[PDB]
Structure formats: structure tokens, C-alpha cells
Amino acid sequence: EFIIRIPPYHYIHVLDQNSNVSRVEVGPKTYIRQDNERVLFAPMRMVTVPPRHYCTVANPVSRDAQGLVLFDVTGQVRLRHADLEIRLAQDPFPLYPGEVLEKDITPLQVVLPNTALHLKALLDFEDKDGDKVVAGDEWLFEGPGTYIPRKEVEVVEIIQATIIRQNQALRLRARKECWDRDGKERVTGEEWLVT
Amino acid sequence: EFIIRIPPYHYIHVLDQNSNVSRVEVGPKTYIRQDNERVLFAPMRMVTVPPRHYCTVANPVSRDAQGLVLFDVTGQVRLRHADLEIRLAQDPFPLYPGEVLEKDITPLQVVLPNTALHLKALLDFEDKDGDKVVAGDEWLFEGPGTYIPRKEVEVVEIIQATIIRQNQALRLRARKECWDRDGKERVTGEEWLVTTVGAYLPAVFEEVLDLVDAVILTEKTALHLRARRNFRDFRGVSRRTGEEW
Amino acid sequence: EFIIRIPPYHYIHVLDQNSNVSRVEVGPKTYIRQDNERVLFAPMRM
Image (cartoon, rainbow over all chains, first blue to last red; front, top):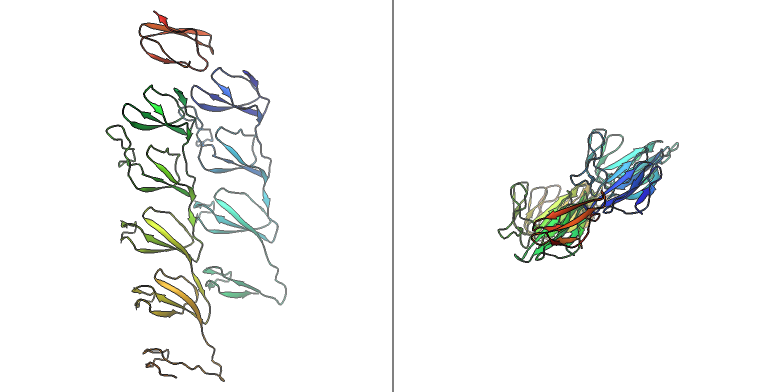
């Protein structure tokens, strides 16, 4: 019980009963616990996400300007409560105490050509383009590429374009006061044609 | 029993029996009680509200100009009795003694576009705009955004705008002496028409009844109309009650 | 067991099992041991 050597690429959590502080230990090293300190469970593999994949862990690690994990005064790990983070392909990071693996290893979604993704901005943020994306905004992301996920952006549905052949037109009504692709204002419920 | 080490991000309440004063202790620390002091219950997690969420706790904490918790002379915590407070996303605050978690962690309501929220001012207050919002006032908050709640403002119902298409009009009567969007006084029960194409949002005091559609006049047809009261029609000629044309 | 308040003019010895080091504590004070640390016997007068 006292002697616990964790296999390579693994970790364990041992609680400091004299301080009520939990910690994680990594690396292919042999570990010996103290009398007060108690391990919580046996080693399980520290998780890695492959390329073109991602995973979400609740309560992300609070980090400094260099990505070094900030530690509390009492020896606890600085977390970000009630938040979700998107982790892309990298080295097999360990799972710190107080964190829940909400979603498993999931592949990056690939968008077929002539297809678009409908996304809604859950919370107000600032996209990399340079626009203040207020919450509730609707997003039309299209193309044959792949979409990297985000915590504050929620995918609504996958939508497919419509083929317009010769001597044909498409009828589409406005769900809200907006502008068409030709640059004309359209009231709610107004219908028009595209040729 | 004497030794109580609360886990990180937790608290407990221990009563000072020599003073009948309860207190809360936070932080990942080991705690030892005294003989007189008695803990009330075992540790339970100190609550945090995530982003785009909120929660309400009865009897909010009375705080100073810097947000520091004011304490009573006898060591009690200064509260605000019979009041409710709205807490938005922040660090996991602890629940002080004498406070009840009335409502759990609830998400911020998102208003769809072409939609409005009907709100009534429960108690007299002053909104951030700069107006004295007397109690009983009615609020029409619309837009595709999200509404942050308030203690003294109560949501009445969620209302949806009405689409007015081509060659159509909407009939809406006044629930109270008011003004229309065109700037005309309307008595209680008075009815009128609006001829603006698109989505039309009803007001708080304007009961929307039904849509009215125009009548197409071909060269082989004509419209027979009897006046209901004295008025002036579209051509600009006065009428009398009962007169037909 | 964890809580040990020695009477005035007394002492106890508690062993630091993480260091195999024993020590004596004096004075009319209340003492709380750690999980690793173990007291050897009950207080007797100094």
C-alpha cells in the first residue's frame, strides 16, 4: 500500500490529510506515500488526444503568461470553475484534481463541399476576425474544410446548399429583417426569388 | 468529531454556544472545534454559478463600499432581511449563515429575434437609463439579445411579433389611455389599424386582435361601405354615421 | 485520540513516523497530533 510505482505515462492522486490538499504526480517514477498522505485510486493512463481530434475537460487549468500551472497558497491548483476548454493534439497532459472529463476523445468534424454549418454564439466574445460577437448571433460557416470547436460557440445544425439548374429559381423568405445577397432590405416574412 | 478538515472549495458552520453566534469557514484548511463550539452539519460544496447563468439567495450579504462583508458587534454577519439578490458568474462564493438558496443555478434567458419580453416593475426603483420606474409600470424589452434578471422587475410573459405582409393591416385596440407609434392619442377600447409591412411588435397596452387584408377592386366589381361614425376616408371626404357610398 | 491536551506541568512524546524522530512538548497547552505522528504514552507529570 505504501509503495506505489506508477507505470510510464500515468499518474495518481495522493491527498495530504494534514492540509486537505490533493496533487497529481506524473512521469515513470517510483513513489512512496507518507503515513498521513493517502492515495485516492490506482494508476490510470494519462490521456492523449491524437491529431484531428479534440477533447473537453470541465474546470480548465488556470495558467500564467507562459502556460505554467499556477498553484494556490495552500498548495492547491488554480482552476477556472464552471468553464470548458477545447484541447487539440499535443503531448499526453495529465488530469489535475478537481477536473472532470466531460467529453471523450472526439474527431474534428469535416465539412463536405457545398455544405455549411449553422452556429449560434452562446456567450458574448470576440472572434479572431476582429468583431464583437454578441451572444445570440447566428453563424454561417461553409466550405470543404474542417471546423475547430469552441466553448462559447454552439453548432445548431448542418445545412446543405440547393442546386439551381437552368431555367429555374428558388423561393426563400426572410426569417427576420435582413439583407439579401444582392443588397436589398427584406422585412420579416417577405419572399423573393434568386436566379 | 472534534477534528473536521473540510475539502478544498467547501465550508462548514460552527456555532459559538457561549455567544449564540454562527460563522462559516472556507479554504482548503484543517479545522478543530472547541468544546463549547459545535458544528451544525458536515461539509458541502460551496456553490459557483457558471457563465450565462445566475442564482438567487434570500437575505443578501450587507457589504461596505469595497464589498467587504460587514460584521455585527456580537460577531454576527450583517444581512439584508426579506431581500433577494441576483448573482452572476464569479468565483465560488460561500453561503453565509441565515441565508437560503431559494433558486438553483439557472441559465440566462435568450430572446429570439422578432420577440419581446413583458416585464412589470414590482417595486419602485431607478433603472440605469435614468428614469424613475414607479411600481406597476409595464416594460417592453425586445431584441435578439439576452436579458439579465432583477429582483424588483418581474417578467410577465414572452410575446411574439406579428408579420404583416403586402396588402394587409393589423387591428389592435388600446388597453389604456396611451399613444400609438404614429404619435396619436388613443382612449381605452379605441381601435385603429397599422399598415406597415413586415414584423410588427405589439405594445404592452395594445391588444392585437386580428389581421385585416385589403379587397382587390376589379373593373367589374365595387365595394359597398357604410360609415360607422364621423371620419375622413382615404380620398379625404368627411362622412356621417350610417351614410353609405 | 487525535486531540491530546496535556495538563499544566506535564509533557508527552509524539513520534514523527515520516522521520523516525521523537520529541517532547511542554507547557499547559492543547496539542493535536497529525496522521503520521503518533503519541507514545499518555501525559505524566514532569
